Amino acid sequence: TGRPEWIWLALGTALMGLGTLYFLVKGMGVSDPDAKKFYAITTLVPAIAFTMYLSMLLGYGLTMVPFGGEQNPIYWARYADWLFTTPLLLLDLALLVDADQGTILALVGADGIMIGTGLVGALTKVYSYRFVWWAISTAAMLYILYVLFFGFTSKAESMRPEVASTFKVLRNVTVVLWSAYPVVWLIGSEGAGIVPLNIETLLFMVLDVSAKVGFGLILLRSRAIFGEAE
Ligand SMILES: CCCCCCCC/C=C\CCCCCCCC(=O)OC[C@H](O)CO
């Protein structure tokens, strides 16, 4: 409670934990193999985020990085979370549209580059270089968003209508929410430092819960997750 952002870390921990438990209960008894994949991916996402939020709340997922002549508090646990949860969210989208394996690898690999370069930027001690890493990570994000809109055209013709509808909604949620992350980083403690760490933590908490629990609620309530069966 010594760090003002503790309240948002505590709320994030609670919301990710509750979301995990809800998805775990909701997925009980699901037998359809396709739906099992979506429940597994979508329950793992907030479960991982729960552990990383808790690690930030308890102080383990925080480190001090010297730059700008200050000791800057950097929550590195965010990147350990996103390293696994962001490819999993992309996998949800890719499986919906029955993406080619090559497209899945392009997405997951670009996503690993996005998170890894974000982590390097977050830990870099030379201030100006932090924004070089931010730019590379943003380029990887833009590549991901490009694929989400322009890499699935060969699947549109054979796509079930409920699949197309749910994918379109989830893709729009993804573009809007994922785009905000580089902005928050750029203006917050890890970039220019014009927004204080407590407001940055609040912003990432709203984004994370929306991108994980909100996204999951939309996906797991849809008929698109079930194979077409009589
Ligand atoms: C001047 C620096 C130039 C280098 C900047 C690199 C840094 C990372 C930037 C963007 C991510 C690149 C993602 C690379 C993954 C591309 C995979 C691919 O090409 O997939 C095509 C295939 O047809 C399947 O759809």
Image (cartoon, rainbow, N blue to C red):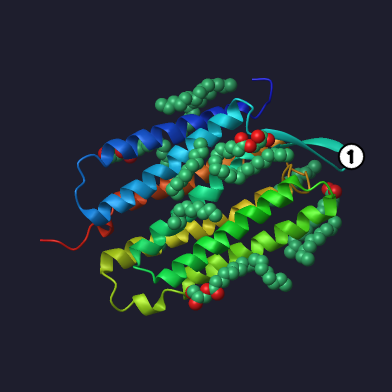
Residue 139: x percent and y percent? 65, 66
Q: The disc labelled 1 sits on which kind of residue? A: Gly
Residue 118: x percent and y percent? 67, 52
- Classify 10 Å Cα crowding around label 1: few (below 14), some (14-19), many (20 and above): few
Q: Quadrant of residue 198?
A: top right
Residue 128: x percent and y percent? 84, 54
Q: Is residue 148 above or below residue 132?
A: below
In the picture, measured across the screen, residue 40 lies left or right of residue 135, that is left
- Taking the spot 81% from the left edge, 55% from the top edge, the residue there is 129
- Give the residue pinned by disc 1: 69
Residue 214: x percent and y percent? 42, 46
Q: How many marks?
A: 1
Residue at disc 1, secondary structure: loop
- Taking the spot 72% from the left edge, 47% from the top edge, the residue there is 122
- Taking the spot 40% from the left edge, 78% from the top edge, the residue there is 153
Q: Quadrant of residue 81?
A: top right
Residue at the farthest left position = 230
Residue at the farthest top position = 1
Instruction: State the quadrant of the N terminus.
Output: top right
Q: Is residue 144 above or below residue 4?
A: below
In the picture, measured across the screen, residue 194 lies left or right of residue 164, that is right
Seen from the viewer's position, the closer of residues 169 and 78 is: 78
Residue 177 in view here:
no
- Taking the spot 27% from the left edge, 40% from the top edge, the residue there is 26
